[PDB]
Length: 70
Length: 49
Image (spheres, rainbow over the protein chains, first blue to last red):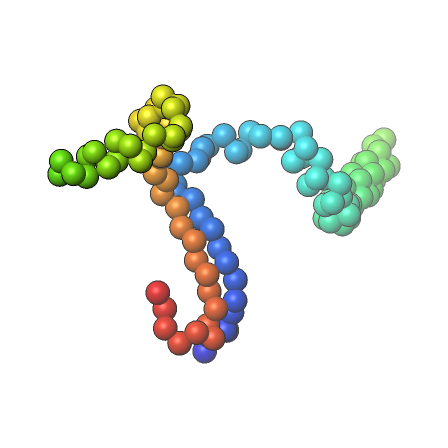
C-alpha cells in the first residue's frame, strides 16, 4: 500500500540557522523572463480568440447603427 | 616516589622545548555546536540504529 524499499543518504540543517525571508526578492528580473518565454503560447491561446471576437461584434454593431440613421 | 623522580630526571633530558600550551590551541580554534542531521537509509538491513 505504501512501501518502496529504498537506499539514499540525506543531510539537513536546523530552521534557526538559515535566512527565512530574503529568498523572495532575489533575482526577480530573471524569474520574470523565465515564466513569460515559456508560457506565451498558452496565453495566445486564451486571449487570442477573445480579442478577435470582441473586434468582430463592435464592427458589426457600428455598421447596422449607421445604416438605420436618416 | 623519590626513586622514580631521580630516574626520570636523568632519562627525560632530550625532548623538545616549544612553549605552546594546549589552551592556546583550543582558544584560537573553538568548537561550535550545530543542529543538523544525517540519515542513511538501506532497507536491506534488519535492524535500525
